[PDB]
Image (cartoon, rainbow, N blue to C red):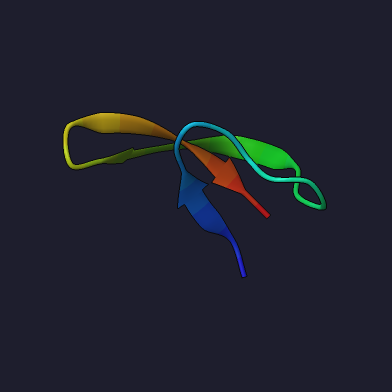
Length: 30
């Protein structure tokens, strides 16, 4: 699965983009 994360992706994931969710910017991580 992919995840919209704050503050960053976690080890074993890569950042592939950005989410906009709940008025906040999140890393798109898979």
